[PDB]
Image (cartoon, helix red, strand yellow):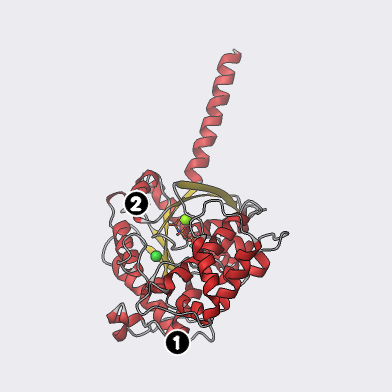
């Protein structure tokens, strides 16, 4: 008697578990390396779980800080033409920083912060930083190098922005579950460098939607994997691969044209011309229905819409009735931007999942 009763209790439990799964939106974050996928996940935690509640991440921030200064300083003599210190008295600091580049488990002594700060204030170091698209530099370099004095304090506690800016590699598949207004979301974060893309197929089962993230600002950079392929070209080629992939033909794509702040900054700097990398930009005109933010520099508007339209040219070329691409301009480190963008996705995501039920 109690045997059949335990049994269909398990079975009522099983049926509830099936309905939870069916109604949970599985969101797969795809995009090339450093496009911003893990930062989007961190924002979902800030907005909808408990964020980072931090002391675990202090070493990661210090490692980013160290990677940034040592990368810039190492690049100075390797650029063509090389970049010289503005104050050649700083050479002994260059020597120190380069000498500790590959020490595992670095102990971050006070001289490290002293030398890093002095070098970061050197106009030559800064001129090398301004050429960083000629080498490989983490995006958070300026943010952390500007607060060396904060990070080095013994009582340093990272802010939420520090944790968002912190770059770590994503080796493997990382899941994050969260609930917004009793709707359940299940986000899958994966690495986006080329070798990590072999893992992506493991997540294609029962996907509700893809969030495809692009570093819009990286149009003048090349990928780490071969130090030759343009990063935006790689993003486009990768998006075409996803849009047309055998397993993902039914799956709609929310396209996050991310790093809008860095793109704005690169446009305003005026050094790196998009048409030097994408010659067709010279003939591109901002669309009639563009909606620039008040005061946005029209050069920025034209840039960001050109990049959007390079992706939409791919997504409009196939799939017309079977899946759709929803573009959004994003700044993944801006919590209020991601709050607004994600809220504007919740209705379309619910609709994607409902249509999936009729197809099954
Ligand atoms: N200023 C700015 N920084 C951004 C933005 N999106 C990401 N970043 C920064 O760019 C770096 C890379 O971001 P991350 O989320 O780790 O990229 P990813 O796509 O997960 N990289 P991977 O594929 O290797 O896992 C981080 O330092 C992150 O803070 C953005 O919109 N604006
Ligand atoms: Cl990218
Ligand atoms: Mg990542």
Tell me the quarter of the picture where residue 8 sits. Answer: top right
> Marks 1/2: CA distance?
38 Å
Q: Residue at x 39, y 49 (%)?
A: 356
**Which residue is labeled 2 in the image?**
195
Q: Sort mark 1 into few (<14), some (14-19) or many (20+) by Cα contacts within 10 Å.
A: few
Q: Nearer the viewer, residue 114 or 288?
A: 114
Q: Where residue 148 appears, x then y in whole percent? A: 63, 68
Q: Position of residue 278 (x, y in %)?
A: 30, 78
> At 70% across and 63% down in the image, what residue appears?
153
Quarter of the picture containing the C terminus is: top left
Q: Measured from the top left, where is residue 173 in percent x and y?
A: 45, 46
Q: Secondary structure at mark 1?
A: helix
Residue 259 falls left or right of residue 235: right
Viewer can see residue 332: no
Of the pair 346 and 269, the residue shown nearer to us: 269
Instruction: Say the numbered circle drawn on residue 298.
Output: 1
Above or below, comparing residue 40 to residue 258 in the picture: above
Rendered location of residue 62, percent (x, y): 59, 60
The quadrant of the image that shows the N terminus is top right
Residue shown at 59% from the left, 66% from the top: 335
Q: Earlier in the sequence, mark 1 or mark 2?
A: 2
């Amino acid at each position: 008697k109690a045997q059949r009763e335990a049994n269909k209790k398990i079975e009522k439990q099983l049926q509830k578990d099936k309905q939870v799964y069916r109604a949970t939106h599985r969101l797969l974050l795809l995009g090339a390396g450093e496009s911003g996928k893990s930062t989007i996940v961190k924002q979902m935690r800030i907005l909808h779980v408990n964020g980072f509640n931090k002391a675990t991440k202090v070493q990661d921030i210090k490692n980013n800080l160290k990677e940034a200064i040592e990368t810039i300083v190492a690049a100075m003599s390797n650029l063509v033409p090389p970049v010289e210190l503005a104050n050649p008295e700083n050479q002994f600091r260059v020597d120190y920083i380069l000498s500790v580049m590959n020490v595992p488990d670095f102990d971050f002594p006070p001289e490290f912060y002293e030398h890093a700060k002095a070098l970061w204030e050197d106009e030559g170091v800064r001129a090398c930083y301004e050429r960083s698209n000629e080498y490989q530099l983490i995006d958070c370099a300026q943010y952390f190098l500007d607060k060396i004095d904060v990070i080095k304090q013994a009582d340093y506690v990272p802010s939420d922005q520090d944790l968002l800016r912190c770059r770590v590699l994503t080796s493997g598949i990382f899941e994050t579950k969260f609930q917004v207004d009793k709707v359940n979301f299940h986000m899958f974060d994966v690495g986006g460098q080329r070798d990590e893309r072999r893992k992506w197929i493991q997540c294609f089962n029962d996907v509700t939607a893809i969030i495809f993230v692009v570093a819009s600002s990286s149009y003048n950079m090349v990928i780490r994997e071969d130090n030759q392929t343009n990063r935006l070209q790689e993003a486009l080629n990768l998006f075409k691969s996803i849009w047309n992939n055998r397993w993902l033909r039914t799956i709609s794509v929310i396209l996050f044209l991310n790093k809008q702040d860095l793109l704005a900054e690169k446009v305003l700097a005026g050094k790196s011309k998009i048409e030097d990398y994408f010659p067709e930009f010279a003939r591109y005109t901002t669309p009639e229905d563009a909606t620039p933010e008040p005061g946005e520099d029209p050069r920025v508007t034209r840039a960001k819409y050109f990049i959007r339209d390079e992706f939409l040219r791919i997504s409009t070329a196939s799939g017309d009735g079977r899946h759709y691409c929803y573009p959004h301009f994003t700044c993944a480190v801006d919590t209020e931007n991601i709050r607004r963008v994600f809220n504007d996705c919740r209705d379309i995501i619910q609709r994607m999942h409902l249509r999936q039920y009729e197809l099954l």
